[PDB]
Image (cartoon, rainbow, N blue to C red):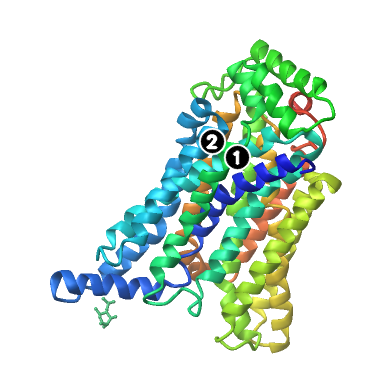
Amino acid sequence: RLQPTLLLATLSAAFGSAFQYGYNLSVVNTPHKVFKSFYNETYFERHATFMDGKLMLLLWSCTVSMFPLGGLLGSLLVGLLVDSCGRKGTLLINNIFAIIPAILMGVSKVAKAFELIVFSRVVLGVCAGISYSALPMYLGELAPKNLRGMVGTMTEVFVIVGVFLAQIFSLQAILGNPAGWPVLLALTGVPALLQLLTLPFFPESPRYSLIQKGDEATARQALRRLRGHTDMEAELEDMRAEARAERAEGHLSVLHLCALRSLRWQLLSIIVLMAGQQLSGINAINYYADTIYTSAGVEAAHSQYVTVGSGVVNIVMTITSAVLVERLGRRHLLLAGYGICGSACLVLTVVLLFQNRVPELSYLGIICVFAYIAGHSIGPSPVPSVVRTEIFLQSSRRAAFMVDGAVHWLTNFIIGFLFPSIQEAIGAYSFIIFAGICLLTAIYIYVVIPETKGKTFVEINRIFAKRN
Ligand SMILES: CC(=O)N[C@@H]1[C@@H](O)[C@H](O)[C@@H](CO)O[C@H]1O
């Protein structure tokens, strides 16, 4: 982001959209006991008696796992909205599904009903899915080729920002109070309101207007504002060319995924990229981090502070990945991140197997956990978000993003509700599976995905064609 209008527009779009995804993704795991207690007190008030712990477990599983389900529905909904309202109107309508549930969760304690907390989780999941499938389109189409990587990475940058802010605000001292959780839950609507107030002042993505709506005039002004001075003649010609080529060849339409043979490899590439992000071990590092820090000598009274430090490392590594996308490229970052993740998983399996015999291995274990956090943050987290939009053309982007988001959310939910059993069924060799999965994903990325840095979309489509 060089021009100030583009930087402000990117900040306003990402802060109100990706922050919802991150915050509602990780705001509930830490203060679980408080919500347990509130549910049980509401049930006591309503029925004048306690209820079974099985109903506690079922209700908690529902309210903690409806967010992936809401995200999956939302991902398959961005379709009906993205090409109907542009990235702009889609992001603006996405704010309703983040403002209404925020108010519902805010007035929930006085209303004395947990349902509003269970239904608002589904609504916020829908909002998060729509945001995750719409914000990358807006950021990629807004930015020029020279600065496309940083603006595209801003999506995951602000996702991690929201995750870190939610981790900070979810501590017992800050807002995890039995009388402070309504504010914690309702804080997710403030960025939504700010984006609703700020974003309309910024221009719609020029590519959608010219290539899809046909209004070159509007595109010109938006570009003038976003691109500033300089020149736009060439940029406009690119859009016109990409429009002419797309019209001549055709576009993806969901119902004909296999019919369009040209983008089959690209669809496979994006599907493989998103699954390798979710099924590549981050769940295990999370489940095993507490045990690793406990064995490291850290008392249980700081296993949190260590989680906050891990979040800080995640933030720093994501920002440095945003900086280095336009310098080292995308393929290099993907390969480096997946290799670091695989090596960390391997050495973590080694230390977990040999933790009891040699207590001195705990330092290597915590180093490996932090190394995995950093490596997954740099390569596999934001670069797929940047690449999912670079490969595909304009009109095919809706179908491509529908498939990509559906796969991402489905893999997220599936792996989330399996590792528990796997952890038990297998032991620590779970990490070898993941470090296998990471190795396979890195091999596929090296073999198939080419370099798309500093290249317009017509070129990148040409490159993929030659691949096969
Ligand atoms: C439902 C459940 O998990 N058990 C709770 C438990 O917190 C405690 O025995 C008591 C506190 O008031 O209320 C029970 O219903």
Q: Secondary structure at mark 1?
A: helix
Q: Quadrant of residue 39?
A: bottom left
Residue that label 2 marks: 403
* Residue located 82% across and 30% down the image: 229
Amino acid at circle 1: Ile
Residue that label 1 marks: 271
Residue 312 vs 398, above or below: the answer is below
Point out the residue furthest to the left here: 48
Q: Does any portion of residue 394 appear in the rendered image?
A: no
Q: Secondary structure at mark 2?
A: helix
- Ranked by sequence position, the earlier of labels 2 and 1 is 1
- Between label 2 and label 1, give the one nearer the viewer: 2
Residue 159 vs 131, above or below: the answer is below
Point out the residue furthest to the top here: 248
Along the viewing direction, whichever of 111 and 273 lies nearer the viewer: 111
The picture places residue 302, in percent across and down from the top left corner, at 59, 84
The picture places residue 108, in percent across and down from the top left corner, at 31, 62
